[PDB]
Amino acid sequence: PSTTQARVVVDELIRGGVRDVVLCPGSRNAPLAFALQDADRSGRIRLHVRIDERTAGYLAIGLAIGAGAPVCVAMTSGTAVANLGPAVVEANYARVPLIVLSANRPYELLFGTQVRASISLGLATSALNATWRSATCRVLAAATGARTANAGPVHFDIPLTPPGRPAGKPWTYTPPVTFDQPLDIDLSVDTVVISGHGAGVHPNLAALPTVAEPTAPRSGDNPLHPLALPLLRPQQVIMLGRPTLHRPVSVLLADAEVPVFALTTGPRWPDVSGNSQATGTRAVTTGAPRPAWLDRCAAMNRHAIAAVREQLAAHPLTTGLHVAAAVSHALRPGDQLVLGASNPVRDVALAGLDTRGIRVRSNRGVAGIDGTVSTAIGAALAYEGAHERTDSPPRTIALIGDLTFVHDSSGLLIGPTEPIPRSLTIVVSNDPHDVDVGALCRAYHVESRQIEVDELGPTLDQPGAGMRVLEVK
Amino acid sequence: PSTTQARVVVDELIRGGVRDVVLCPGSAPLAFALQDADRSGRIRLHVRIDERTAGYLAIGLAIGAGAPVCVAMTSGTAVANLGPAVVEANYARVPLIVLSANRPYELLGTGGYFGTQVRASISLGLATSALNATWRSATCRVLAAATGARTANAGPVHFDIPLRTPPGRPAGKPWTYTPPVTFDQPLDIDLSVDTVVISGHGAGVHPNLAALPTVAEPTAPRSGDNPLHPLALPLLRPQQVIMLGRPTLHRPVSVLLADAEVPVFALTTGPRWPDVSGNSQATGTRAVTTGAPRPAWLDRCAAMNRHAIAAVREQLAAHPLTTGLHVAAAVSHALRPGDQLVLGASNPVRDVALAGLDTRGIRVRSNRGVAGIDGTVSTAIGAALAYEGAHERTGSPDSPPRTIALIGDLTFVHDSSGLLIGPTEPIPRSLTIVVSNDNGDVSSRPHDVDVGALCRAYHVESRQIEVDELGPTLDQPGAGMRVLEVKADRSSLRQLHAAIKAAL
Amino acid sequence: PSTTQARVVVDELIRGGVRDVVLCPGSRNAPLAFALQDADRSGRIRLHVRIDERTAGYLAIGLAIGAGAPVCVAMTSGTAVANLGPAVVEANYARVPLIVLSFGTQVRASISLGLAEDAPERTSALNATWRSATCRVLAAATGARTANAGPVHFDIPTPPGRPAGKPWTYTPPVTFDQPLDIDLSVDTVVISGHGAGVHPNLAALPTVAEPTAPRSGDNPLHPLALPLLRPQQVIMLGRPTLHRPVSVLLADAEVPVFALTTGPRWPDVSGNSQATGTRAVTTGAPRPAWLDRCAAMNRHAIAAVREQLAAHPLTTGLHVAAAVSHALRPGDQLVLGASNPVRDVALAGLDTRGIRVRSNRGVAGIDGTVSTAIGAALAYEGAHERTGSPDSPPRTIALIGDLTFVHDSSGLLIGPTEPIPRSLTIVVSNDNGSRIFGTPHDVDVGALCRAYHVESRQIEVDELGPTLDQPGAGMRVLEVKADRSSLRQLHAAIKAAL
Amino acid sequence: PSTTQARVVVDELIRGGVRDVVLCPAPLAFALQDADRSGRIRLHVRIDERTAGYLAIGLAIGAGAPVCVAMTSGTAVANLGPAVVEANYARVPLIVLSANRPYELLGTFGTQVRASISLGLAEDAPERTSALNATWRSATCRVLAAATGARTANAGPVHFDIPLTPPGRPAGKPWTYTPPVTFDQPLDIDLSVDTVVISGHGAGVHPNLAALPTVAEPTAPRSGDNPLHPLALPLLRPQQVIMLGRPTLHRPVSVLLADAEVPVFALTTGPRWPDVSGNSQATGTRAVTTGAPRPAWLDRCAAMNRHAIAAVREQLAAHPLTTGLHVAAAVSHALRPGDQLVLGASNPVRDVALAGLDTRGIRVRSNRGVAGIDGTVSTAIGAALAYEGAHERTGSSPPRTIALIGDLTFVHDSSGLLIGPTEPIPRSLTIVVSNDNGHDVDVGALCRAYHVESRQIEVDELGPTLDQPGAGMRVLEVKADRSSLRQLHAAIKAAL
């Protein structure tokens, strides 16, 4: 009955690319928990257990953004819907394929806008196997954006052995969708590119002056520091993805005289104060920038880069901007960088990190302090899972403010049977607070140490024994 | 202020290609702005009393020629009465813009209702250059959601303006321009495996499947000329099926699409894919085709198509009394390329299918989203009006092409108030409604309604005629709008269909 | 399996006072209908069948407000929830006990019954679950514990009940009580709206009562007299919505407003309200000079209306309302369409005592008035029928405009197998509807009535009274043609004469 | 505009009895400090919104007043989710104050609240500021009424959105005055039929039932002199059950209430009634009694009660190891009139029920709405603050607040100890952590991290240590054994 379906659902999820499931102990109990246990011991799926339902949601988000695969989270409680809320909101705005599994019972008496779909299974053979597997492929497709190009969370409810397809394939195969919507842009108009979360890669814009957020993959080689923007007057703005970070960016995007062209990978598009003139997925370009425009942009960029480096050296104290500058100087191709969505991602932008070669993650969907520790842990687990399937696991470095670390300190309560990352290092920046991070870390039995900003590079260079936290005052 | 907001919203909707607005009067500034645009000739106002039939009138105005259409509400039972039309517009993917006028402080003083059905539910700001951009941006975003400019999933949008001319772009341009989106998802299909195409509502055109035997619902656009009658399907052994669009009509289709042992390939124009098969093997938007169908497979399917058609026509002629199936056959024979055919969503659309209508050259419409009784008269009127609008716009001085609707008496009676049109409101010039009047578990337990009295009540020309007169009567143009009633028998219906079955 | 579930659920509904159920032919559902069919054959319930789902909702509205009972509508289709929407909204704002059998915000409860489990082992404890939930539905719908009746949504996807037919979970109707201190020597007017209670200790005060409000006393104050007076203080009963002078006064920030309601909800106009309760604990008595002023302005309002109607040659809708008012008798039920008829009856001065006045004042929509009148007449006749009393059923008289008639003309589509009222008479005041606001139109009402085989007659206003005194011809429609051109100047002539 | 809008709603809230506000951090924010600086409200600041919601719940249950949480973020409302569920089921008047922007959201829960009210976008209206005063204060008076149950008798959480000083009434009165509402629904009950009273969360007080044997959850206000231990109930067969409030605690209660043979009478303070019994025969708010209980019934219940009490007491003494039940019993024996007791909602509340606590003169709090582990630390802090604050207004030593919570619950909500140095801090809150291990978490280190006084003590020191106040907030950790708990419970049941 509900045992046979549970095993078909799990098998179909695995065939759809689910490698990780996060589970919470329940007031009742997890839809298909035994079938998940079975798949874990088999090596087919990796299970993760957490007491806190909220940090469980962010652990799954991390497991999704670390290598780009869909992830399941099995609710089990009367508190569960409400605790996963923040993670579902983040998964919606950041377009993260989070599958929320649950169970409600038909035999007993009885997320809305944020999810891409709400699918309920038939309660309860050969034909029924086909109805269970199609439903699960539909869950996966909506979650991964396979048809919509708009990934996001999905609520999948199971009301509480038979073969799938030959050769391990999804019951219902849905190939890669190409979403495409070309836009004429003339590049001899003085243009700046603003790159935000979820931006695509555009080789025909690679030469333009580009203000790129740390999570935005860069198409080229001509960066423009954000603090250089108020010193320039673009006639035209190309906006990739959804940029939120800086005030001169918002000011420029809300200037009625400056045409903004929005280029996205999915069907959503943003505005600031309704001044977007046109949408697309890519540009068909004519012209080339004025050399005088490029020179001026380049000069204002050196000028801004210089004024940050000077005022950092000018300051005796170690601010959070010094910490960001030292982390950036220490990263190397192949690293994953996970940034807290508040000050870390802003400080890394100002310190001028060159992100090419680096996999940068941040919960930019709602930019909440919430959940950064579990997100970093989940990203590291999934990223190291990807490397294992190809020498030593590549580093994951996380930058987190001290309030954010203590807020999500529950992410550190990991039982000894649960998967732990090999190469995660969390750098905490201690900028009215009073908490002792070192006591916090020993309470949860996590190697921790205070260090000066000068020594972060060398300390980061030496592989640590597992999960560690570096506190910087 | 609210007057500025309403004149901006209207101007932006016109740049989006809204040509027709349906207005339900109540209580306000939006109403005058539409009055200005209509008097200017920039749009076409339609005023209706009943909010429900107004939504179905908008459906018809939208599917008549493919444009986005607005329904403006100014009332409290307003959104609730547009429910049925919003559901229809959801499942049939119709760009319907529901403009509401919410009064927030008054609902508090007593002491997104549509929810999942709409593509978007966007509140405008309660009523200088900054607010112009906020208002026109919100409106271009309403328009794109409704037409599927970026999603390829058109449908209904809730647009709420609460209540207590700054220009748009040069050259009549939409504020935020959204160019053509192509959504692409090829599937590899081998045509040497014995294949039939099932084509439903919303199906795209596929020239590389033109040769295959195709069971096409009346509203599906055909890609070829190798039709396969739906009653022929159970007499054949296809090894795989290509599903276009969202088919719902026939039991042989549903029984075949539930055939666990037959692979189904689902091709659609947008992101949704139908549930009807649990053995769907692959979903996509177009086929990449290896090979070709065997000539012996084509000949067998062509032969069985001819056989099912002949059995239907033979049993019709041997059956002593006029049924709705006879009426549908007679309508089908009377149509000609350029005609628009509007079909009631219950028996008429099935009966036209059984009668074997050849739909190439004909624009066939039917509310196949939920296939309700409601609104068929208003849908046919709006479809006639928009389709005539496009032909007027072509320059040809010729009489507008015909719109012919086929609806049952119960549906006609139930939406008869769709005929209540003010003297100053747009009337179709070449709309003919054929009413197949066959009178019709505790509910099962029967009308006796006088259809000609009903038309007299709304001052619509109406004539009772026999099935053999229908063709010649339809050939003769009449009043702009008219109703032709054909009496029919429902008791012998079971007997006719059993005869058709046994004759195969 | 299911059969047992539907039979107990129907049985509990009948125990809970449900006498009428409305049903639509639909694509799905039979057992729910079978259990209802049995109960209809045996005379326990009366089933009504309708094809238009919107019509069915308003028919059930009428069956509920005619004699105060909960009523079920049983949905059966994919268009059903969406068509039942307008009636659920009306039921919500007018606090009508409408049970919807298979909305979110609009309903008092959304209950799902257990999918029936096929084990006769547990049929005695799982009887009790089914009846409890049914009693939970009835209590939410009738306001048994909340004092806030409204629509409920009840999902169903021979073991007995309590002895003596008692409902399973007995909830004695509640007393909700919240006394408010009010000094009646301050010059007070009472504004009585929809859903108002009866207050004996306020009976002497000048009272502007909407036609659906029960009169507490014998001191009426015409709404047109209100702008000619300065109340120092207002007592607002229920939820008044009718007149702009009332909205102006209720809005006035200088005038304290005391809201007295029968349920937990309370209204405001412009957040003006100083206090809320359910009853007045009064000190004092109205100053005689205040009662004199109010009575004198009441007379001038009444005189201005009747005189200017007589000096007006063309028959308006206000003439029709006046004639219907003059023909009413104690024991009649009056049903008013929600726009002009209820306003015009208030203007013409109806004394409502002895009269049961119904109107869909929750959202005041044009929709559903024909079926609401039909439903109200059926439930009212059926109550009087259960007194055993040998006199023939009392008249129901509905007054509606032309537009409302065509808008709900589908309500006249009644099979010969269905309950039809014995003494219902629908007066249509036909005003023929500028292009948007005026809504000009021509409908032949008599052609429409003939299409549905309903007796109809177009008559003059003067014949209305005599024609109304006639015996019951079953169900009839009486049309009186009316002119809206002269309406603007008749109203102005009343004000100037005021 | 926005600025004066914020100032007036803050002022109406204060008129309607709001004394504490919890702020997660614009004009609404600034309206609160001036009222906090003026001493009109006491403002509390928190960084974690889930934590802020549970602190507010504690502030509301500590003394029965309405409490606002003011929030300004997008993750804001979602993070307040679990506290809103608790406030719904426990009927806690929590006003969720929300401030955010529609255009900004465009340019990128509902069933739990008693009301969702969006206030008007501030319009300057220099000449309409009078009618804008009235529309904002009225709406704030609706929010307070819906929250406190002033007309419904059904208190709960309210969503009050303000999107993005003109005087109130004379003499500090609220804009719309709602007097006391009594909801009354008499029920005829004959007490000569053998009756047990089961009193749950939210139970009222009924003098005419005082002589009946009564199984009372720890949070149930007691009205009688005749308790019946919960372990005694399986050993009896009542002929009638009177169910007070919403009982959730014990499996023998569920089994008896689901027993098809036993008529159940439901008496509640509000219009809701529990569905625990499918055989609920009737529901009301008070009983009108005929008769009186038969002496033989009263004798049998008193004897069963004595056996249960003796079984617990004697098997605790004979047990060679400290368990959570020894800790619960030691906390019970150390309580005195005036104390406030806060219980974590899994084991502590059950263990205090079996230890057989006498709740007379004791105010007992527990998040019995959904009985989750979330926010127990913050609820206790909030209950202590509000309880202490109601003692200062009486004009009289701050009374003790003692909290008993398991170690996993303490770990989970330990970040509720993160309290800024300007923020209000309890005078006399002692958290007793009963640590049977559940993780490997050092609880003492956790208290270090938040700079909270902490000691590990043995169970027989707890009574002594509890009158040694020291810091305003302290944590007392009692190590306990979980390995022998099944045997202790079996020894108790076997001795019944």
Image (spheres, coloured by chain):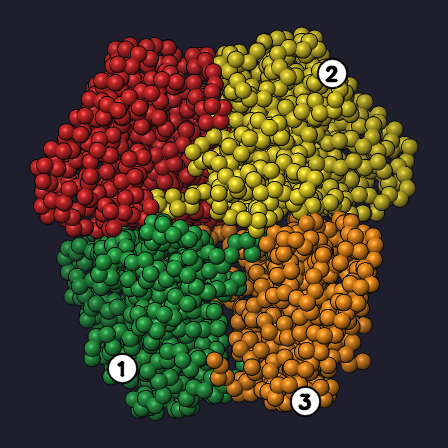
Chain colours: A orange, B yellow, C red, D green
The chain holding disc 1 is: D
Query: Do marks 3 and 1 share a subunit?
Result: no
Categorize mark 2 by other alpha carbons within 10 Å: few (<14), some (14-19), many (20+): few
Of badges 2 and 1, the one in the foreground is 2
Q: Quadrant of the C terminus of chain B?
A: top right
* Quarter where residue C406 is shown: top left
Residues C179 and B504: in front is: C179
The chain holding disc 2 is: B
Q: CA distance from mark 3 to mark 2?
A: 86 Å
Q: Amino acid at mark 2?
A: Asp
Categorize mark 3 by other alpha carbons within 10 Å: few (<14), some (14-19), many (20+): few
Where is residue D105? Give x, y as percent.
56, 56
Q: Amino acid at mark 3?
A: Asp
Q: Which residue is mark 3?
A: A454
Q: Which residue is mark 2?
A: B398
Res. D167 in view: yes
Label 2 sits on a secondary structure element that is: loop
Answer left or right for C249 relative to C187. Answer: right
Label 1 sits on a secondary structure element that is: loop
* Quarter where residue A359 is shown: bottom right
Residue at 68% in and 67% down = A231
Q: Which residue is mark 1?
A: D398
Answer left or right for D273 relative to B86. Answer: left
Is residue D358 placed above or below A92 in the rendered structure? below
Residue at 33% in and 76% down = D385
Answer left or right for D269 relative to D345. Answer: left
* Quarter where residue C333 is shown: top left
The chain holding disc 3 is: A
